[PDB]
Amino acid sequence: DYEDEFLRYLWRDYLYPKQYEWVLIAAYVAVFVVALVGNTLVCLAVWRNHHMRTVTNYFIVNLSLADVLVTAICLPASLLVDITESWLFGHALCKVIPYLQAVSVSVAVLTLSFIALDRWYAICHPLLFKSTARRARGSILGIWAVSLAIMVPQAAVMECSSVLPELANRTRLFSVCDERWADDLYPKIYHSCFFIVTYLAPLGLMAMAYFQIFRKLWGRQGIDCSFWNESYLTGSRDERKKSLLSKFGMDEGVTFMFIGRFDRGQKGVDVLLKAIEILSSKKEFQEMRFIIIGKGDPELEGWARSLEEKHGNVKVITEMLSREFVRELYGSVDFVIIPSYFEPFGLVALEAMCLGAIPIASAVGGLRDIITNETGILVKAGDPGELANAILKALELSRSDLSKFRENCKKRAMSFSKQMRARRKTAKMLMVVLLVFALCYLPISVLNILKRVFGMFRQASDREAVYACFTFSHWLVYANSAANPIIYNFLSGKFREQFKAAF
Ligand SMILES: Cc1ccc(-n2nccn2)c(C(=O)N2CCN(c3nc4cc(Cl)ccc4o3)CC[C@H]2C)c1
């Protein structure tokens, strides 16, 4: 009958001294200061400098401000509650602080989502990529609006109660803050939807987005620009060409060069050979030199050697060469032909371009991205005829200086390589941030979903370790706020620079 009543009456002053408290305090103040100075350093770094004012960094600022909010208001309250098992604040703050916590979690997740979306467009759909500062500073406002709108039920249900309800004796030592619902459907529904909205759906979506992003960035680390440059070549280019041609027993002429596996339906050496057969006539053919380098199918090798013994301006190399010598080739020949069928990386285009070799390549895959206007010739893949015509145009261009074209090739290759490297680094950082986020909010979510929907931890002496789980989960949640600036400091060069300069 009056068991809970009487037991509460007897044990109401039984404080149980927790063995590990000073470590919790130390952890909380550590996280507190680190999150504060870290996130403020983020905000300062971005706001002050102009090169930092990027959409990604505007969002990162939004995230940092969210974390600042949480760290300032909710972290100390969470510390006090978790240590003293009591609510030491007003009835108003009992609604406000958990509300601000929910809202800020929302803001954080949505921010990461917009980061992921922005990067997903920039990388996976470059053509549709629209991302001005006006969009960001206006989308952030939408994030805060929705976040401040959909969290009002939690503010509503937050109540500050103490002694067991329906009890005449309102005597108490301490009060506590918790949720008060009517129908038991309401808390289950709201908390399941809270887990879904603030964790499940956006982290799923972002998992997809970063999956596609990393799939698009995979294997694209760029090339060694320190190796692939003309600096290690001696003399003038035309004299290197003259030396090269005379070394193969040929005379001066507009030199084209293929390098790749002799494949049927990949590197397209067959397209090249066919194109040479097309060029076997015409007046222009004698003005051309061809150097076909590679090794693959015996049929294609024979097909090449036949041309090497038919036309005096065609040399075939099935010999194994060194990178230094390949470099020397790229810095000697006039044009390099990449008749690929689906070339996803086009490292030959980059490596050759860095050495002034002008690319004549099939408009497929990576090549399309690398070779733009005023920096190469692009061909419908597969068609030997259009390739031959491209070679003819190359010849008609060779009756001019071509030097600025080559310098354009160099610049394009270098900027492209640097861009893909920067891209890689950025995506890596954002990935790590998302990951650390997920791991940080995982325990509190598994606990909340196990406490508010699928039963609870309310029965008997099944509470002592559960409190410890909850305190740890809370601390972790706040530790994320300290984590992000550190992540930025290890994985973003510009943030490193600004974090150093701030001292
Ligand atoms: C302390 C803390 C930290 C993070 C939390 N989180 N889990 C998921 C998202 N974020 C929670 C938590 O379990 N939340 C979020 C909001 N809630 C809440 N209660 C709080 C009490 C204090 Cl002292 C300070 C902040 C508080 O936020 C009550 C509802 C419930 C869903 C609690």
Image: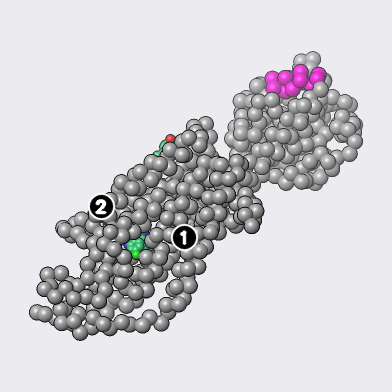
- Quarter of the image with the C terminus in it: bottom right
Q: Residue at x 76, y 31 (%)?
A: 407
Between 348 and 4, the one nearer to me in the picture: 4
Which residue in the structure is indicated by mark 1?
Answer: 480
Between 432 and 291, the one nearer to me in the picture: 432
- Quarter of the image with the N terminus in it: bottom left
Image mark for residue 153 = 2
> What secondary structure is found at the residue carrying circle 2?
helix
Q: How many marks?
A: 2
Q: Residue at x 81, y 19 (%)?
A: 399
Callout 1 amino acid: Asn
Q: Which residues are magenta?
A: 389-400
Does mark 2 have its CB less than 8 Å from ligand 1? no
Q: Is residue 48 visible?
A: yes
Residue 147 higher or lower than 336, as above or below: below
Callout 2 amino acid: Pro
Q: Please state which of the two labelled residues, at mark 1 or mark 2, is closer to the viewer.
A: 2
Residue 88 higher or lower than 15, as above or below: above
Residue 87 x/y as whole percent: 30, 68
Q: Are marks 1 and 2 in contact (CB under 8 Å)?
A: no
Residue 118 x/y as whole percent: 48, 41
Q: Residue furthest left?
A: 1
- Image quadrant of residue 231? top right
- Identify the mark nearer the N-term, 1 or 2: 2
Q: Residue at x 27, y 55 (%)?
A: 155
Q: Residues within 10 Å of mark 1 (few under 14, many from 20)?
A: many
